Image 1 (cartoon, rainbow over the protein chains, first blue to last red):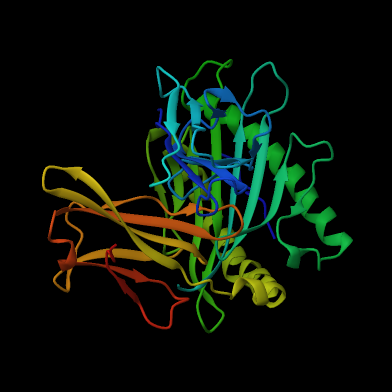
Image 2: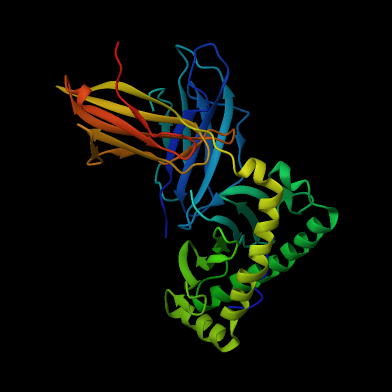
Length: 9
Length: 99
Length: 278
């Protein structure tokens, strides 16, 4: 299952 | 930055004149992902070219497989013409049944 | 061929003035594509790219499709952010790529994890193998790096990688192990082509093999020959199998001293073959 980066650049 | 496409033109099955087959144009190692791919028969666009969905590899370069149905013949020439920003000119690779 | 793997390749391309950025996410188990999402679809959702994935229920697809929407957000936002960090004009097309996932060993535990990012095809930021530190390619990436060290992002990713990535991989393996753990040994043959005065080209063909992991080498008098050996990239036949060839230039009349070696996990014994006339 794919997931989120969650954190921003 | 721009990466120049690498093109292989080849058949799915060992070529046999008169016997239906699949012609592949496998294009790799290019960036940006925008690309145009035409498959040619005797210098003319094959109107039914099925293009796989683009992915990219572990080096970030993109790849894609264009394919169409064809029937190898003693006289028909097949090719793949590719247009990309890395290239000033479109690149044509002819099908060589020895490669 | 090695440890089992689950990998995701996600990419977003901005198209200024032509609407939303295009977003594509592709999933691979053991290098086989099994799941795909494209934003330019009529009904953008994750679709099976493997028959053993239609064993999954309705809730699965809707859930991961939701994840896809969230990801689209993230990608658009950070596309714009990077436009910021690199001081670039807003009407250009740019690419943002994310690659991530897990290699697991025979025990079933995390062997290797991946979290990497590229902008315009060039490395941006990558989780080191310790799964604790970041490699940042340039100054623009250092910002994100300080930001992410401050936020403890590495622990979050490490937790996902050691945890559910592996569990999902195990699950998938369990569903598709009949088709994933299958081998197709290559059919090998050698062709002969005139090349120049006294010189011929010998070409070793390996056709119809699965998986794609293969080694082709030449041999002069039983000894490995790779010097000036031309290797093409393993290419898809389009039916699930692969092709590869390897060529050498050889003196005319001396072709009998050369042998081609094919190594593939489908073969019980390696293939050794030569140019067989007539």
